[PDB]
Length: 183
Image 1 (cartoon, rainbow, N blue to C red):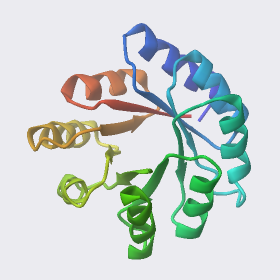
Image 2: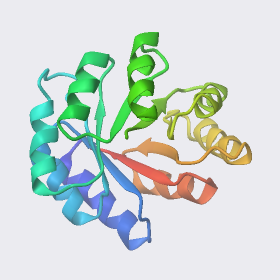
Image 3: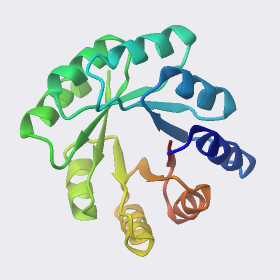
């Protein structure tokens, strides 16, 4: 998970013409650089550091307009929204309480991004209101099959995550619109 390699993936996807590139990191400085290089969606992870909202705060001040935040903890997600995140990432393995909070805000504002390794799960989340459906099957055959099926279902804002721009480009070709470089 090397930053210089990650930035190069963003650069290559930009050269290929992608306009909805995302970048996942725990460091606002790394995210700011990815932003300058072509990433429009900046995902603050810091699933290790608690007050990772400090990172959201700094990116907000720097002027990024699409900041995402991942936590399984609805209280953390809500704080991140308050500090300027507009995309809250919830996971299939999360407690039901996580979606419950992000759904309240989504009605009122925020977008919900749902990560599952089962495409039928992702479809249900789409039907239940999720704005962004993240495919991250490490098997590429299965992952690209999930992207294809979500496109067939009409699910919108399909995302795929990889450390390799070539896999992201294949996902893009098959129907993914958001391409997450995992730094």
